[PDB]
Figure 1 (spheres, rainbow, N blue to C red):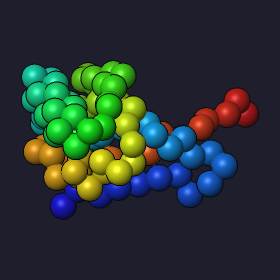
Figure 2: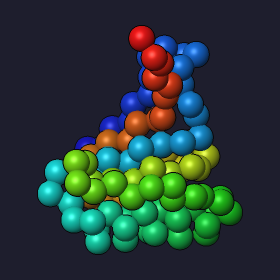
Figure 3: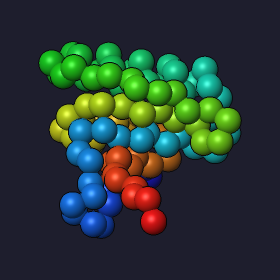
Length: 92
């Protein structure tokens, strides 16, 4: 069900940082528990992860610095809607 997305403009992609977007009515407490679950599952596989930010107010989810190797595992987490690789924006 959950899908993955990355910027179509290759020079503007920022691999290694992902926005994990949870389903619309996901509560902040569920977002935090999901982020900790990802960190625990990643740690068991020998990967270091860092939760940079937990989102609430507009979209539920979190920002994670982690290897892209963990994306298949992250897409399987409860409440996940989609995951987007971070990318650049520029002054116009």
